[PDB]
Image (cartoon, rainbow over all chains, first blue to last red; front, side, top):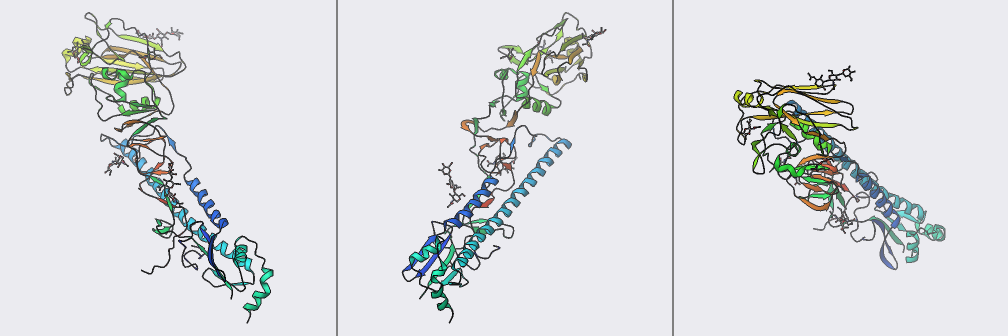
Length: 172
Length: 321
Ligand SMILES: *[C@@H]1O[C@H](CO)[C@@H](O[C@@H]2O[C@H](CO)[C@@H](O[C@@H]3O[C@H](CO)[C@@H](O)[C@H](O)[C@@H]3O)[C@H](O)[C@H]2NC(C)=O)[C@H](O)[C@H]1NC(C)=O
Ligand SMILES: *[C@@H]1O[C@H](CO)[C@@H](O[C@@H]2O[C@H](CO)[C@@H](O[C@@H]3O[C@H](CO)[C@@H](O)[C@H](O)[C@@H]3O)[C@H](O)[C@H]2NC(C)=O)[C@H](O)[C@H]1NC(C)=O
Ligand SMILES: *[C@@H]1O[C@H](CO)[C@@H](O[C@@H]2O[C@H](CO)[C@@H](O)[C@H](O)[C@H]2NC(C)=O)[C@H](O)[C@H]1NC(C)=O
Ligand SMILES: CC(=O)N[C@H]1[C@H]([C@H](O)[C@H](O)CO)O[C@@](O)(C(=O)O)C[C@@H]1O
Ligand SMILES: *[C@@H]1O[C@H](CO)[C@@H](O)[C@H](O)[C@H]1NC(C)=O
């Protein structure tokens, strides 16, 4: 996609993550673990539901129309009846084809976008206490126990607390 | 000794291929079908009023072929014509058959109102062994075959004004004998004529004597015509022979009514959309079942499948094998 996170700087997805679409993995002194990010996951799902509901919106109700199959050869009038129906069908078939192509390109791009949004939000949260490795992971330059990691994930990480510890570890 | 925090996204083991602007096939975590491609094979009897023609075409029901008498005064949203249908009365043609079928189908009713035409000096209620009604000879229930009385057939001249606030449809005809002996035997005059008119328009038909192929005991034919009389207009019928007279008029309506050719059976269920293949669901925007449809239907397209991506790009782990 256009943002280069999904199938880009993030090598691959996690089959292990069944409780969410986007999220976090960590290593610290206490071990490893995984958590879904509810907010980014929901933003993507809401947009996809939005487009799905727009697409399946009932619009067409027709009653008496023209005949479209014929048991006799008749010539001019029948040629025109068939041509009209064939023209309609081709235009509608084209619309269907284009619609899905555009929709799907956009769905791939907006999901890539949400991944990138989460990544940039996390980087901004960590301020000068971490560095972008380039593969979707931050190296955090201080002791971050399980309580600290959860603080990053639920938006309550105060960067000033750990700044001196981290700044020292970074600049050698 | 610090910590790593990795951002990521989900993947699934079994993804789905979709089309995009740049790729004719690319894998996403999930997708949904936008083309309805199957039917139950059955026409749901609700919510549209379905009238099964069984052995009858709409036109035979209209004219009143005896085996179609059960359709008298019937109404429908969708009249269903079956491929087994057959005619079993006097052999006939309808110039512009398709138009008469269309306008009746669209009107949605066969309500017939008998009117007191006075046919002075002719014999009424003629019939034929081509059109048996019970054990004896008969005719179309809505038509009145007029023939000579004594040794004369006078100039018939009758009128019927429309003083109602609705349009009247009159079905009438002209008889084409096979021989000159038949023509003079039935109508005295060697050549007949039928003129049916309103204020604004007129039709005149000259019969043509001659053999046509034998159908149910006869080489002769009837040709069927129609005339709509609007409120404040008047019907006049003028003939010196060969008139197959109306007995009254059909009440016309406008609305959602139509007709469909189908052999699908009618079943107890609910479906807004009907095709000749049967009813189809209408939760999807497109369908590939049949270009012929009735009701609230997905639009017909040529594709048998179109997948709308409902998830992100699916990227499973780099594969060791
Ligand atoms: C991924 O997308 C597919 C669609 O391609 C989803 O499959 C569909 O799942 C729904 C369940 O939400 C099924 O709906 C069913 O509706 C009937 C009739 O009203 C109802 O009686 C059932 O209880 C059921 O809810 C549907 O059968 C199914 N369709 C197909 C073609 O498989 C799937 O759920 C989505 N998966 C994820 C992880 O989002
Ligand atoms: C065949 O039958 C029709 C219908 O009965 C006859 O048409 C009628 O002909 C008379 C003339 O003889 C018309 O009379 C006129 O009526 C107006 C009132 O609207 C009056 O102001 C005039 O002074 C005049 O008397 C009558 O309107 C007309 N009817 C219709 C419906 O047009 C026709 O004459 C008959 N012909 C034969 C040869 O039997
Ligand atoms: C619904 O009925 C139509 C029309 O009878 C089917 O299409 C016909 O049958 C085969 C299908 O491969 C074609 O070779 C014919 O040319 C088709 N006829 C017309 C007039 O299109 C159609 O397959 C049926 N579809 C379903 C889902 O039952
Ligand atoms: C009104 C009338 O008398 N119709 C007679 C007809 C007509 O002469 C022909 O059908 C015209 O083509 O002939 C019959 O043999 C028939 O068809 O059964 C007997 C019938 O009584
Ligand atoms: C058809 O309807 C009209 C008026 O509603 C009525 O006079 C006529 O007898 C009806 N015929 C039958 C067979 O129900």
